[PDB]
Image (tube, coloured by chain):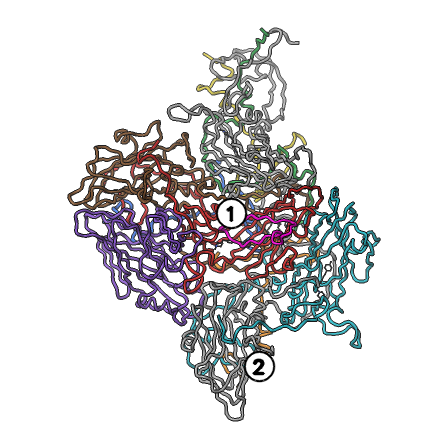
Chain colours: A purple, B blue, C yellow, D orange, E brown, F green, I red, J cyan
Amino acid sequence: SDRVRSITLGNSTITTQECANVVVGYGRWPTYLRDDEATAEDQPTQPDVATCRFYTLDSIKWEKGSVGWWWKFPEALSDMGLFGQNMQYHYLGRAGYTIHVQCNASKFHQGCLLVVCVPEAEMGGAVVGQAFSATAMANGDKAYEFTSATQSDQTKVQTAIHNAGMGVGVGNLTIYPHQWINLRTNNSATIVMPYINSVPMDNMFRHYNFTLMVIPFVKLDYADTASTYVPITVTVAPMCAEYNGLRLAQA
Amino acid sequence: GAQVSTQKTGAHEIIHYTNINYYKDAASNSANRQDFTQDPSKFTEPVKDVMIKSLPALN
Amino acid sequence: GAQVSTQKTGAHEIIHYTNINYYKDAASNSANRQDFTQDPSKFTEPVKDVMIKSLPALN
Amino acid sequence: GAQVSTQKTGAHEIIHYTNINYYKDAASNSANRQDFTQDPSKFTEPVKDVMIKSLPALN
Amino acid sequence: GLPTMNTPGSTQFLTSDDFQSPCALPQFDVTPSMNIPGEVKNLMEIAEVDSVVPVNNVQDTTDQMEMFRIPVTINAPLQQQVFGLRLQPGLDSVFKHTLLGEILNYYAHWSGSMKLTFVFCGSAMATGKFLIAYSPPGANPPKTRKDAMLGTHIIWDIGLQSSCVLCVPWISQTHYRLVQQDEYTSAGYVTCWYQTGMIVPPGTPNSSSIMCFASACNDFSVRMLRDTPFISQDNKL
Amino acid sequence: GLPTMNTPGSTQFLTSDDFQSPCALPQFDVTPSMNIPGEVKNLMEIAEVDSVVPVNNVQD
Amino acid sequence: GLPTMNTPGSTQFLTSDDFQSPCALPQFDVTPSMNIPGEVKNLMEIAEVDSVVPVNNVQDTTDQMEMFRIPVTINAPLQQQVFGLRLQPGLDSVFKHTLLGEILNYYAHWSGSMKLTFVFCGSAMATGKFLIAYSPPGANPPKTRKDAMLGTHIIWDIGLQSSCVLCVPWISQTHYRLVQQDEYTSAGYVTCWYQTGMIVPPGTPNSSSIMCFASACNDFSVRMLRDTPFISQDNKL
Amino acid sequence: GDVEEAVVHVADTMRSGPSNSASVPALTAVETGHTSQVTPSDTMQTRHVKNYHSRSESTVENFLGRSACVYMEEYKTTDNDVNKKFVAWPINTKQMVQMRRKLEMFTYLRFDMEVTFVITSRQDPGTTLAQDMPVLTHQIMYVPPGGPIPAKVDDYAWQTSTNPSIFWTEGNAPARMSIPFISIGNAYSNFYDGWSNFDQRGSYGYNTLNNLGHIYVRHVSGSSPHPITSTIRVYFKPKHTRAWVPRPPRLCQYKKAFSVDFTPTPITDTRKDINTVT
Amino acid sequence: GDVEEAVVHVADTMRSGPSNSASVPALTAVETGHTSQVTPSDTMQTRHVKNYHSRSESTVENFLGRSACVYMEEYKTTDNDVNKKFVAWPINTKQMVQMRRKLEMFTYLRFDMEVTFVITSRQDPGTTLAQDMPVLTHQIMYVPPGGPIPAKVDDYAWQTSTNPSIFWTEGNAPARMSIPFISIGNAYSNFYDGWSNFDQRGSYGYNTLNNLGHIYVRHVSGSSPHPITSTIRVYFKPKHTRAWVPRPPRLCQYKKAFSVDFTPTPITDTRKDINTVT
Amino acid sequence: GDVEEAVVHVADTMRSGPSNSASVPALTAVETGHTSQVTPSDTMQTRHVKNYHSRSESTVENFLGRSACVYMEEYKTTDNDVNKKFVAWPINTKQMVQMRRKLEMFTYLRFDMEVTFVITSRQDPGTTLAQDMPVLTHQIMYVPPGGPIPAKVDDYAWQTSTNPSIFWTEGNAPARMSIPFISIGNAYSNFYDGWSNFDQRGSYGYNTLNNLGHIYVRHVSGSSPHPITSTIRVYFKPKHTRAWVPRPPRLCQYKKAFSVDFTPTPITDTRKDINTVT
Ligand SMILES: CN1CCN(Cc2ccc(NCc3ccc(F)cc3)cc2)CC1
Ligand SMILES: CN1CCN(Cc2ccc(NCc3ccc(F)cc3)cc2)CC1
Ligand SMILES: CN1CCN(Cc2ccc(NCc3ccc(F)cc3)cc2)CC1
Ligand SMILES: CCCCCCCCCCCCCC(=O)O
Ligand SMILES: CCCCCCCCCCCCCC(=O)O
Ligand SMILES: CCCCCCCCCCCCCC(=O)O
């Protein structure tokens, strides 16, 4: 059977018994930087099993009225294990990611989720012509919630779900690497995202490489059961991570 | 140092043109709009395991 | 990639000209008004059975 | 009497151009900005005795 | 010097010309190229990717996300219509803003076949059958399942495989069709009807939803680059 | 550049000239050709076909 | 004559063009060439030569020559800072007017490593050790020797060899950096700290001075020729 | 291969002498729809003649290979009426009678097109004419079907990013370009005996198949203190042409630009009697 | 070697007959993120068709290979306000909506640039318009980042010794040139989800990466007795282009030239009901 | 032989590992006047890097291969003052500051010259401006040292028989030509630390070696009823260049066109203290 997959990174393993295939970015597997593309001169560090491992972020609740959530990386993992320490102590970084989302329910539940990774997911503020701080869009590993109605508070991003906070049709997100979690036949989605950027390396505290979004296209529904909510959990594992430019640790 | 290549035409109807470069910078050349290679697999089949159309998608 | 061909002249009086294409689209070429093939049979003899001029048209 | 030479381009991306001189004076030619030879020794190592980087500068 | 004579069109500025021009930064050294993942060499590659179609435009959608879900129910009057739409990928409101309609709106002519994929997002214990039919152009669209069945159609059975594909063939009198479609270049209709009905066991929701995905086949193509009408401005930004 | 001198007739528009001009729709794909019956390549072919002559022009 | 059509850009005067033109003095005989010593074929050769850096810009220098000397003393509080400066070769006042900054100010982009050479100009009997460190870009510059040591650094021992070289490596996210540097293209900081302190025997001066020399490595380069902003005029000379 | 090397004459008379036989070339039967192929040598004695005449000038390529005006129009640089300061012409070849008749001799055509634009300007009369204005500039814009259409001279649509356009300055040669075969079908159709709807209702005639687009022209930024009027002429020149199914030339005068409507006309002129030859 | 010699078609339908087997090409699972590769031959009987259509016009090179206006601006030959007699434009492609949307369909781009300048002049209205002025001349100056910037029309900075410039006279063809790939990075970025400072503070968005320079324009020495106004239009034409990571086209109208701010918009238009097809 | 066929990159980093030995590349002695040749690989561990950067744009040929203005001047078509109707400029490169500083970075230079002339005209203000004047024409005259010099616009010297000259009409492209290396010595000298007389008296500095000649400009025959003012700009563009003995760039502002006189200037700007880095 091809419906069972096992993934092993470092000292952690992920086993799924009802999973779809695995999506690999744009057909490109993560790899280390080549000699003829590098620009920095000093030797890069390559913590391997220490940084490359699965790290489970906090879990969320899925209710009948949920609208969606998003996470920004690597700011989500900025304070997770030795990966956060390496980010803090280094000026440059580079790594691919493997994203796994878990969501299980009985055969009597119905619903559908869209899992997509959006590189360079620039977002606009609620009030056009008014800036927002670096807290309405990333504050660690906590999830940020979309809104059904138009956002009105000026200190946060426009959370209109149908526009996805990017001024584009929410239904056209299929272009990016993505997967669906249909409760009929699937419980989890796996995406392998290589390093995508315009430069060989970049600072992981100043730049958000990509954004992860989970949007329920078909709202959850059930009847006559003792389960009131369906938890969702997200797991991420850096791959082929390397750093450069050691310095004092960013506060 | 003159390049001779075919020019666009129809299915069943000297279809040659000559080009010469006058400047020392490649940025001054004309558009190279004669390339027609494409591959949609990167966006249509991003899966890891190859799936055959005839066989069931799952199991 | 230069084409040399004869140009129109009289019966008993270097009658050559050179042409080169500069554009990548065949629609940009000059008119090909040097073709003189014609066949009036399609409109003058549309009958099925061939009729000989010398013999009677019918019977 | 036409000179064919390569034109500037990038690392991994017909890169040829033709030049002809029309005037009888060499001063009328275009700039010869395609020379890239350099030697900083005249200003960086004007010493008489050669000094090895690894060994001590003096004694 | 060499005798010459200027022909008509000299000193004109054509926005779609191909001529060499002098370089303003001679002997400039460009940054070395790097193979970023996900290179696109043709807009058709984008055009072949699926996208969700907002079929439920009922003029009373207080929630925008409701546009993407096609309602379904138990105890459905026998042989009922699920949905009906006109096949104008570049003009009809349904396909106007899709990932495919956006691409076609930059062109004037199009040709080739299309793919419509339907996915059932109900309970695992639910079951049913549906008839999806494509009706070529005609003087009247179908009004019953008996009329619909006469054209190209496929019987969809809901089971472990949650998705079925309806391939719309390219049936036309001309090699190409106008994006701004009219009566002359009409393309037909697409409709879905109940085949057996939806049956659910006790302790399950009484309603379900379906979603549709639209994309182009490998024989699709476009032509005549025009400017899209969806975007406009009144003053300089 | 190359020395040149314009001759009389430059910048004139002659309705029966044969010159190349840029294409406004580069790399356009034309519809495939089809051999429709009854192709005419010379007006003389039309000229050789019979036609009824109105000889009885009696003004009445 | 030969049919022709003029393209856009004809009759324009571009200051960076390369075209042939007639000679106003035909068949002129030029003076024979002579190989004068010291031919320069590239501005980089000039750029690679050392020059004194005016590090002591204390806003209270009544004597201009004092700008070139870095003070040092005996009985220095342990782990003290000797000097600190920002690494902006083309923008910072320290490197602005140096033999290297002048060259960079004629360009817009630069890349490569840099060399900083320090020479001790104290007494022959004096001795000491110094720590010189380069801190890549960050949210905060170092404030103590413990913070400084974490980055690239070299321990300098004063002896018969009176000069030591700190090679600043090229660590950047982009292949090039702007001469008009900003927050995005910041380059870091350079600082010097006491390692052991300066000790002198009886009958010697209680103070000494140090000098710094700046130059470019063999992998340095520049790009985009621009006009320098250091020189201007108000009326014709 | 720096070079690549790339005389039809009308028939010749042949000598004929006296004849007496059962063959009767002169007698035929038009009922078959067949045009007789008899020659003067078959009905009288003739000498041998070598004819060097050629039918080169009668080819369709040369017959249709002439530029002809198809549309004129005037627009002012400044005026109170917004619609009067620019032109908007739906493309069609039925506007000018000469070219319309020349094209309508064939049922189907397939050719490339060469378009030339002639623009002239004149200063409008008034009580005060003294002014100084630099050379004017004009923009020609082509909008394929379905594209946005400008509503005023200074509309945003004039920032063409995909629509081809030409900018031309007075005093230079007329603008020129080429257009390929841009028909959805396999050939242009001068006539269409059919309807638009499938139930035989709606538009009738060749108006149903005209979906070529529009052409817009304006002054780029010229706005004189006093009005100035400009006129543009469009010339079409078929190239690489092919024709099918010839049809008789029209006899009645044209009366509509998008219909075949006409008034009955006499077949030809009259004379005193059938024998009058003077 | 005086000469050096230097046809892709869409797929063809293949004949298909009746089938009855366990294979089910029509059935798939979109949950995998994989787009079905089914063809009409797999779900119905089809004839053999040879298709000659080509996707030549859909290539990115042709799609982006059109000149589009990016900036307009007016400056007077003579006026009391010094700042009104010349233009100073920071280079950016976000000013015009059509080209902005066309470019924003991709995340990263790498191309050469071809810049064309269109300049027109008109004489301002007034109570006295009679004057005689020879042909005007214009200077276009480009200042890379960090270079000196002129503060007036007759400033010393207009004596460019290293900064490229063009001198153009009215009545001739528009000015034109080429510009290479001048990005510090390996490719232009239309979007940048990041900040300027390392502590996640300061400027946000693509405004942080815009360091292309400025463009200045003036009348060389023209100073008429009466005011004359001139307008300049800048056109960009990418060449030798490459794109990565396509993204969905924008839906909401633009509102800022240096931000993604927008207002929520409906997904699409509505109709009477789900069954309405008329 | 109809054709005749006619990539230097900066150094590459090499991998370096830990080291512990008596060699001390970091330690040197600047007293020798020798600049250290150390590389980052000699003081820290480094990876292998292939660098494709090139120093093409830093060559002297490209650095000095840009046209720069060197002289401006105004002359009127008609005026009461005879000396005001024509220009007389002694050739020298010390007039404009930018080009002067660019040239003064080297002691000796040897190059060909390319001269371009930009001429513009404007009609002077007055109480009556209405007039009609055909296109103007200008004459540029070069007088090598010792030749006759005109004293008025209509002098006999304007009949050049050996002195080269150019006649130019407004509305066409700017005039252009080439000039060879015309120095009596083996190379131009930007500086001359010496005197004119043998007893160390007389002129001092580079003014002694300036014997290039003069340039004269006039209106050929234009004489308008009302004054018209014209301006000429001269641009120099070295070609096929060679330089020797580089010298530090100037720091103080220029004050004289034929002398090195200056005012003392601070070495550079100041800051709060030696430790300030913010
Ligand atoms: C129904 N009629 C059939 C004949 N057809 C003739 C015709 C063919 C081509 C054109 N092209 C006009 C044109 C469009 C754009 C452009 F840039 C230049 C020219 C017009 C008429 C008319 C319709
Ligand atoms: C952050 N945006 C990324 C996209 N980039 C597009 C762009 C690329 C090149 C130019 N060049 C302008 C130009 C500069 C000098 C010159 F001589 C001619 C043209 C502009 C925009 C914009 C920034
Ligand atoms: C003493 N200075 C040394 C440097 N030298 C620079 C220089 C070189 C050549 C010229 N040529 C001017 C010229 C003369 C005649 C002509 F037709 C065109 C240009 C000027 C300066 C100046 C003296
Ligand atoms: C600056 C180049 C000017 C070229 C002028 C036209 C070509 C003249 C030579 C004939 C073509 C042969 C070129 C070649 O040898 O490749
Ligand atoms: C864009 C083409 C420009 C052609 C310029 C004139 C021809 C120069 C080359 C001499 C002719 C040889 C052409 C050939 O090799 O077929
Ligand atoms: C005054 C020179 C005019 C040259 C005109 C263009 C070149 C024509 C000849 C073709 C190129 C061959 C030149 C050669 O034999 O080297």
Magenta-tinted stretch: I71-94
The residue positioned farthest toward the right in the image shown: J156
Q: Nearer the viewer, residue J46 or E69?
A: E69
Q: Is residue I102 positioned above or below J60 on the image?
A: above
Cα separation between marks 1 and 2: 64 Å
Q: Which chain does the numbered disc 1 sit on?
A: E
Residue J259 is left or right of residue E71, and the answer is: right
Q: Is residue J172 positioned above or below A191 on the image?
A: above
Query: Within the magenta stretch, is there residue I79?
Result: yes
Mark 2 — residue? J32
Residue A228 is left or right of residue A93, and the answer is: left
Q: Is residue C16 visible?
A: yes
Mark 1 — residue? E236
Pointer 1: residues within 10 angstroms few (<14), some, or many (20+)? few
Q: Is residue A2 visible?
A: no
Q: Are marks 1 and 2 on the same chain?
A: no
Rendered residue at 49%/20% (across/down): C45
Query: Within the magenta stretch, is there residue D25?
Result: no
Figure label count? 2
Rendered residue at 82%/58% (across/down): J149
- Kind of residue indicated by mark 2: Thr
Q: Secondary structure at mark 1?
A: loop
- Tell me residue J6's x, y (percent): 59, 58
Report the disc number at residue F30: none
Q: Nearer the viewer, residue A24 or E53?
A: E53
- Kind of residue indicated by mark 1: Lys
